[PDB]
Image (spheres, rainbow over the protein chains, first blue to last red):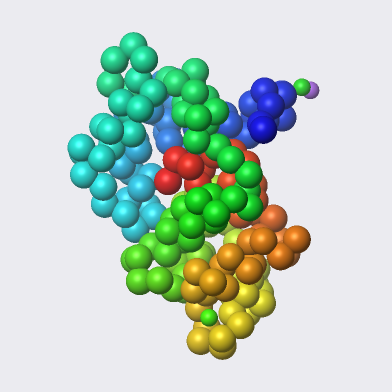
Length: 148
Length: 19
Ligand SMILES: [Ca+2]
Ligand SMILES: [Ca+2]
Ligand SMILES: [Ca+2]
Ligand SMILES: [Ca+2]
Ligand SMILES: [Cl-]
Ligand code: NA
């Protein structure tokens, strides 16, 4: 379970701000799309609108901070749950080909606000890459994400 | 280790659930 502590609220605000690039306190479909596109995805307007509709209690077409937190309360689970690890793999695997490359990892990490140095990227890939193909598949990813 | 800690940071602020 997550708590509404000052520290946690600040973390959620950081996430909200990633989307709310104009700082107007609302996340639009345009803003959702810009972030997803930065991760190699190209969702339809329908897909973007559906995400808003999940928590758009006032029906104004955008997500405000309370609605965003309602989404987090509904969706968020343990960091090592099966569904969070599969969803994390899909995000890092920009092209959906079943392997996370160094280029993908670097791109996704910086566009989500946690830029890695090339040394941090190479280190993560090297250590997670058990089969030696230079990339990280789902099974390797699970191992990396669960190993303590 | 450090890259993994950063991934955990992204998870705990909900960015995997959003993306
Ligand atoms: Ca906005
Ligand atoms: Ca709304
Ligand atoms: Ca890939
Ligand atoms: Ca591999
Ligand atoms: Cl507190
Ligand atoms: Na405090």
